[PDB]
Length: 223
Ligand SMILES: [Ca+2]
Image (cartoon, rainbow, N blue to C red):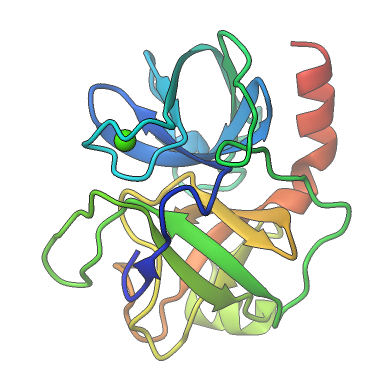
């Protein structure tokens, strides 16, 4: 997250860190045994880390649970990042409390102008690199589809939306991928891609979760 603020320990209780010996992507807890992330975060041997603030210090609220199964969306296209969404099933159910909690799926798509919360442990610089150890937060609005397509000609599908600031300075970034975009207490987006980070006229692009609620619910119900 570039230009954000320190969330505070366990103030984003649905935020997960995906770990393969190191943090490499975010994700969102959507019930006690399932996590949603980005398909471009796929790898084998994922450990899901819940209840994290400082990802380099054991602080006492963590739950570490291995993935038993990963399901990349059937139509994921790694060249265009269309359908950039993946489901991860935990080997055992998480213990839910005030600091580890699930985020609700949306019943409707959010409109442009809605304010959302984006969070992650990604890079905090637009040039160069600095990775934080504690979770960072950013409040940002959903941009109109017209602004989004004008910023990224020929690249925005109906499964993507833009959020952020056309002036630049505030954005998600590398290492935030897979993490949540929450608006009005519902999961509306997944950190997916962008050109650089926090660059003028290049806002973040996010997977549009409301298009996938049917697939998510059907998949969870039979796996
Ligand atoms: Ca920790």
